[PDB]
Image (cartoon, rainbow, N blue to C red):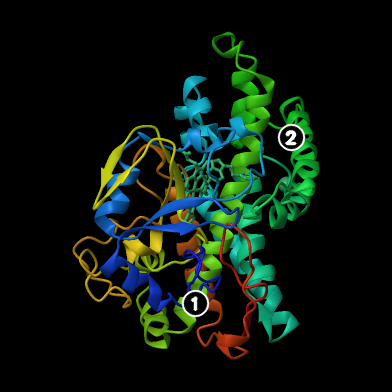
């Protein structure tokens, strides 16, 4: 009997990789799929072909936003925002933005530790079960990014609540996304004019905005940087830490090891990054030329989806890919942060967020365990991240 073209994404579950991924990688590591919009795309699932695509700018991020292109999903932002990093670079702002979002600012790591410990103390006081997503990982991400941006902690929750819509992976445009986007842009425009905001990313952007060397950079770009980096950083660190905590809880031997030897936590987090399923969709690129990828000649104008867990569970690059092994020879060579032109600018901050969050959790609740059977986690659908709606634990 006839079947439709293979549809992506395969599963919204972030606690297991579908067997279909390895079968695809082995039989057809670049293969045609249908996205939720109905568009066809090339799904790339081997490490070698994923890196090839991400390292060839002729597979363009920016052009995925072009009118009439085959789409993975509907834009939730103005099309120029897809090229936000490119616009930042063209405005002469890349170095300043990068420096503002490193975890090395004085007191930043102590802020993370203090915040994590305070959130955990509150959970211990409230008593089990505790929701490690809504009452730990996401508030820690939100507090971190208010600090990094230089904006008041009390503004975090409202900005955060845009994100369950802003990072939707939808077949169609989302009216609420524009409502929240325009509102959050207005907020950050006000931040740039707010004399109290003198630290962090927005403090620096506010200064550069009045510097004659940036007098022709648009106010829209300055505001957009704030919304984009808050949203990307918070959704990415919150979702990654949440699904990392699941992987850690499901490995009590690793939890005990990292609890007893915290110096191993960075290597543990690198492996948790490698096996992380937080990205719900392949990374999209639009071909701007005819390009050979494996056995397929990708044609100009076609959509390519780089499946991160395809690369990161590829046994030809990461032997025994499903196992967390702290002594791999190539531990940071995973694609959790992408690769090439669009490699994540917040990679160092995301690493520190997770390392400190896990260190604090293991000290405060060494006996942490799921409080529900793992299958009972509710996996958010049609979203750019895989996350459980609640993460109930006991300890
Ligand atoms: C505070 C900012 C920030 C943080 C923190 C952050 N991201 Fe990023 N990330 C970005 C931005 C902005 C981009 C777009 C870069 C570009 O287009 O050049 C990006 C790009 C990426 C990409 C590549 C996307 C592509 O299409 O090539 C991946 C993958 C990624 N981030 C994953 C993560 C993960 C995983 C984490 C946490 C563990 C994280 N990011 C934390 C802001 C952030
Ligand atoms: C693929 C998907 C999304 C993006 C973005 C914007 C991400 C964002 C930020 C805040 N609210 C909503 N979305 C920039 N480059 C991208 C590539
Ligand atoms: Cl504050």
Residue name at image x 42 percent, y 40 percent: 342
Element at badge 1? loop
Q: Is residue 289 above or below residue 154?
A: above
Q: In the image as oriented, which residue stretches furthest toward the front?
A: 1
In front of the other: 289 or 50: 289
In front of the other: 386 or 70: 70
Q: Is residue 261 above or below residue 300?
A: below
Q: Which mark is residue 182?
A: none
- Judge from the rendering whether residue 221 lies leftward or rightward of residue 265; answer left or right: right
Q: Please say whether residue 352 is visible from this viewpoint.
A: no
Asked whether mark 1 and ligand 1 are closer than 8 Å, the reply comes as no
Residue name at image x 64 percent, y 18 percent: 218
Q: How many marks?
A: 2
Residue to which mark 2 is pinned: 185
Q: From the image, state whether disc 1 or disc 2 is nearer to you.
A: 1
In front of the other: 19 or 335: 19
Residue to which mark 1 is pinned: 15
Q: Quadrant of the C terminus?
A: bottom right
Element at badge 2? helix
Answer with mark 1 or mark 2, whichever residue precedes in sequence.
Answer: 1
Q: Tag 1: Cα neighbours inside 10 Å, few (<14), some, or many (≥20)?
A: many
Q: Please say whether residue 23 is visible from this viewpoint.
A: yes
Residue name at image x 52 percent, y 36 percent: 100
Where's residue 29, x and y in %?
30, 61
Would you say the residues marked 1 and 2 are in contact, meaning their CB atoms lie under 8 Å apart? no
Where's residue 77, x and y in %?
66, 39
Q: Is residue 324 above or below residue 81?
A: below
Where's residue 391, x and y in %?
63, 77
In front of the other: 210 or 296: 296
Q: Is residue 253 above or below residue 198?
A: below
């Amino acid at each position: 009997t006839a079947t439709v073209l293979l549809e992506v994404p395969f599963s919204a579950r972030g606690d297991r990789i579908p067997d279909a991924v390895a079968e695809l990688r082995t039989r057809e590591p670049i293969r045609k799929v249908r996205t939720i919009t109905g568009a066809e795309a090339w799904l790339v699932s081997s490490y070698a072909l994923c890196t090839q695509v991400l390292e060839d700018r002729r597979f363009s991020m920016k052009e995925t936003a072009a009118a009439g292109a085959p789409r993975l999903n509907a834009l939730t932002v103005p099309p120029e925002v897809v090229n936000n990093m490119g616009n930042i670079a063209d405005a002469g702002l890349r170095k300043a933005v990068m420096k503002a979002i490193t975890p090395k600012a004085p007191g930043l790591e102590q802020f993370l530790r203090d915040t994590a410990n305070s959130l955990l103390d509150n959970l211990i006081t409230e008593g089990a079960p505790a929701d490690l997503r809504n009452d730990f990982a996401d508030p820690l991400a939100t507090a971190l990014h208010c600090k990094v941006l230089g904006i008041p902690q009390e503004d975090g929750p409202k900005l955060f609540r845009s994100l369950s819509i802003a990072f939707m992976s939808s077949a169609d445009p989302i009216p609420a996304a524009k409502i929240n986007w325009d509102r959050d842009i207005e907020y950050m425009a006000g931040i740039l004019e707010n004399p109290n905001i003198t630290t962090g990313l927005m403090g620096e952007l506010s200064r550069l905005r009045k510097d004659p060397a940036y007098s022709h950079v648009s106010d829209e770009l300055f505001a957009t940087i704030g919304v984009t980096f808050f949203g990307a950083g918070v959704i990415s660190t919150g979702s990654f830490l949440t699904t990392a905590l699941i992987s850690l809880i499901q490995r009590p031997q690793l939890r005990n090891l990292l609890h007893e030897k915290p110096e191993l936590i960075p290597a543990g987090v690198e492996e948790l990054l490698r096996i992380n399923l937080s990205f719900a969709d392949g990374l999209p690129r639009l071909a701007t030329a005819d390009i050979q990828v494996g056995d397929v000649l990708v044609r100009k104008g076609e959509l390519v989806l780089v499946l991160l867990e395809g690369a990161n569970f590829d046994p030809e690059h990461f032997p025994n890919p499903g196992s967390i092994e702290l002594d791999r020879p190539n531990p940071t060579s995973h694609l959790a942060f992408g690769r090439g032109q669009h490699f994540c600018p917040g990679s160092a901050l995301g690493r520190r967020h997770a390392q400190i969050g896990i260190e604090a959790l293991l000290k405060k609740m060494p006996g942490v365990d799921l409080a529900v059977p793992i299958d009972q986690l509710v996996w958010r659908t049609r979203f750019q991240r895989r996350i459980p709606e609640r993460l109930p634990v006991l300890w």
